[PDB]
Length: 226
Length: 215
RNA sequence: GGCACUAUGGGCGCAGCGUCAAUGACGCUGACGGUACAGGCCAGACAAGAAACACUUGUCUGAUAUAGUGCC
Ligand SMILES: [Mg+2]
Image (cartoon, rainbow over all chains, first blue to last red):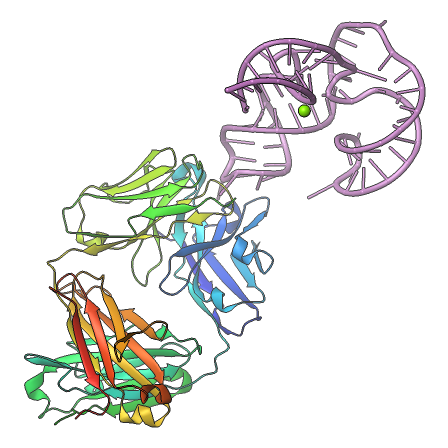
């Protein structure tokens, strides 16, 4: 039970930059195992990066990182390392370190994984979002309910938080996954369906909080009528 | 050459009690050095099967692995509600290692058509030089859903982006959000902005439209 | 990759000469080359060792081999 892996060292970094991730093992001596790195770009699948062998210290790398990344271990610290050099936007991912098990107990399957540390490579500067109402109206009405929302636009880096009516409104909310625009800034929208009969009586205010740029924005969304 | 691992299906809809078989095909012999992993959203993967057919310790017995040559199948004898997840095969026969692209197991329900909504750009936005038009498809099933923008009946390519929610925990439907991004100059060169939605629950494709400058 | 045929300086022959993680191998040229052996070295695959490789110890194969040719 007591086996655990803790990745650390992630962060933002510009293209061409470098970063060193660490992997603190506990519950076992790191000298007798193979240690791997596995990454997962946001919304994508797993991608094996590198590994180091016990007793030999032999190292293996994926094609997409050969010549830029270096895995190593310091067995006196019980820690593994991933030095990443001349990083590229394609390297943006959650980076996992994993233990390959003992041969006789689990073959070569990775039996323990850390919870990962996030590496973001971007040219983008820190930038608070612009918030724009998605006004309810006809063309956003389906019988008894109307849809309405806020467009949270052109921010970096992730994440934003969006609440409706200062948290009081939660049911019917869909806050969509953000999409990364070719400008390198993110954009998301958040929408809630409500009884159309309440559009005249209840105000609706999306609260957008972006701690990286230390910005808080409250937008009242109002119906469009004629 | 790198050994390729390619899984099938890439997504699979089932209900509790279903027998599920996910396959993965190595591009060359990988003998039996194949592992299967389960990953739930926001959590790190967990090992299920090692050496292609050995149940990893502590893993429920309904999971099993199976091999014929380069054909690898993970099956779940009887799906339980905690089995909805993404699964991965991995070859560790040779360096560099390879994962398959992953098979998502989602909850099957009856077909639900999207209710489709459209939102013209805000006045606040148009003041800024940008025009964003947003199309919402709300609470539908299944997830496959073509969203097609038309501007004065011209089909749009290359200027829209989509995002989909995860399957809802309560009605296990989806919701999608398509945004058409235009320069303000481009937006004022046209009249009729339309969202065409194509989905299994609709008899024929539904469209929502507006004319720039409508009250 | 297989099958048949041909030939074989230990897988390591002598002597120089060059490259390399040099009580090793690898490539050159020269000269020599009746046998058998035996150790030892070495190469290749593999097993176990907390072990994919490397390391240690062990196992199997090195004429049941290895070059050439022909054929599928
Ligand atoms: Mg010839």
